[PDB]
Each structure stands twice: as structure tokens, then as C-alpha cells.
Amino acid sequence: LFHSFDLLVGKDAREAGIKFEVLLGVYTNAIQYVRFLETALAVSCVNTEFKDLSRMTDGKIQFRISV
Amino acid sequence: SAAEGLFHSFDLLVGKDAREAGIKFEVLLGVYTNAIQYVRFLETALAVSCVNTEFKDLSRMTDGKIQFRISV
Amino acid sequence: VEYAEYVGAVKTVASALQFGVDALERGLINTVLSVKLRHAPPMFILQTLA
Amino acid sequence: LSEMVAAVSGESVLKGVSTYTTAKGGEPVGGVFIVTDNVLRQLLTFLGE
């Protein structure tokens, strides 16, 4: 019965053992497990796995704007 | 609470084949101990002090009688 | 779960049965001893009358 | 000592098999007497055996 209740209570069934007492009902919560690809504001940001931020120590980037 | 001293073995999930939420019903098992010693009337030493008869219909009898005739 | 109810009721009914039987046996030994006590004169009278 | 054993050993829930048997007779051990060394050295002489 899902557990290890044999040596705590003993071997005999007439003196000791387990028995059903109460059927209780509680309500578990459900939480919406959001992810970044599942939500819709991943459209605005193309997201790649850089996998180590420490490589770019320079805080600026060069844009080559050609008109 | 009523879950203050009981183990629980399993739950009852209401038709949710891939969900762990909702209304859960748990079997709150209980421990029990039958602290008793099996004594019989014929197992004590008091049974020497009586002669016991299995009289299956004593509610039907209303009175008893034994006559002792002493020959002095 | 109904099998967990069924043996949980069997273990209650057979227990109350064997707690009605041994209650009757202890009642029997109690009333035997009370019958013996009702027909029990003290020792300081049977010391002389016997 | 026997009055202590009679005063302690009574109704107790959650029982089982005869735990802690000895070697000579094989009987169950009823209880244990924690004591100091002076009373241990004395109570193997007042009892002897």
C-alpha cells in the first residue's frame, strides 16, 4: 500500500495493522507554466544561445549602416 | 485539521490522465492496536471452583431446583 | 479504494465481535466471582461455626 | 526491583515479536536497569548470581 508500514506496527493482523479512517479532499493549485518561446513577445526578440556571456567584455557593438 | 496524525497511502485523481492538479481525494489510513489478553473461564484457575454446563436455552427456564434428602 | 474500504470494515466488525465476546467472558468471570462473594461468610465467623 | 518491574511493565500499544532474547535460557528481556558503577558493583553481590 505504497509504503513501508510492516516493521513499525508488527506482523499480526488481529492485534495490530492498518485501517482506513477518513477520506479527505483538498484542492491542489494549478499554475500556468509559461515559457519564453510559448509566449508571444518572443517575436520582438530573436533569441540565440550565447552559452557564455563572459566572451563579450565590450559593452558596445558596431553597426555598419549602409543606405 | 483531521490530517493531524494519519498516514496516507495513495490519492484519487478525478479522471486526469496527465494532470496532477484538481480535486484530490486521499486515503488517510490509520493505525490500530488491539491491546487484549485472551482469557477464558476454563483457562483461569477459578474454573476449579465451579462445575460448568453448556445450557443452551437458559432464557426459557425461569427457576431451578435441586432436592437434597439427608438420611440422618 | 473500495477494497481499502472493505478490509477496513472487516477489521472493524471482527474486532467489535471479539470485543463483545471477551467483554462477555470478563462479565462471566466477574459474575462468577460476585456469586462466590455473595455466598462468602467471613473468616472470623467460620473460624468458630465450622 | 520486582516492585519497579511491576510498576512499569503494563499496558503498552504497538507491540510485536519477542525482541532481545538472551543466550542461556532464550527468554525475552523485560527491561533494562541503567545504573552507576558503584551500584553495579553492589548489585552483583546483593544478588550474587
Image (tube, coloured by chain):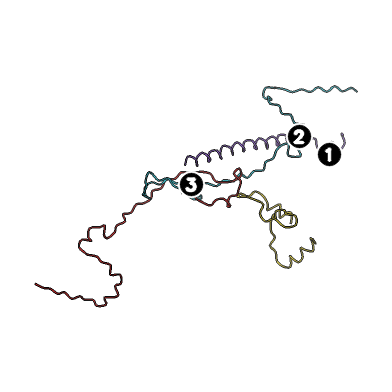
Chain colours: A red, B cyan, C purple, D yellow
Q: Quadrant of the C terminus of chain D?
A: bottom right
| Type of amino acid at the residue the image marks with label 2 | Lys
- Image point 48% across, 44% down: which residue? A22
Q: Nearer the viewer, mark 2 or mark 1?
A: 2
Q: Nearer the viewer, residue D34 or B53?
A: B53
Disc nearer the start of the sequence (2/1): 2
Residue C2, position as x, y percentages in the image? 47, 39
Left-right relation of B13 to C9: left
- Image point 54% across, 46% down: which residue? A18
Instruction: Tell me whether the residue at label 3 lies in contact with that at label 1, contact meaning CB atoms closer than 8 angstroms.
Output: no
For the residues marked 3 and 1, what is the alpha-carbon distance in whole angstroms? 62 Å
Q: Residues within 10 Å of mark 3 (few under 14, many from 20)?
A: many
Q: Nearer the viewer, mark 2 or mark 3?
A: 3
Left-right relation of B9 to A7: left
- Farthest right residue? B72
From the image, tell me which residue sits under label 3.
B28
- Decide: is D45 above or below A15: below
Left-right relation of A42 to A19: left
From the image, tell me which residue sits under label 2.
C36
Instruction: Tell me whether the residue at label 2 lies in contact with that at label 3, contact meaning CB atoms closer than 8 angstroms.
Output: no
In which chain is the residue bearing label 1?
C
Residue A35, position as x, y percentages in the image? 29, 59
The answer to whether tags 2 and 1 share a subunit is yes
Q: Residues within 10 Å of mark 2 (few under 14, many from 20)?
A: few
SS state under label 1: helix
From the image, tell me which residue sits under label 1.
C44
- Decide: is A63 above or below C24: below
Q: Nearer the viewer, residue A15 or D4?
A: A15
In which chain is the residue bearing label 2?
C
| Type of amino acid at the residue the image marks with label 1 | Phe
Q: Nearer the viewer, mark 3 or mark 1?
A: 3
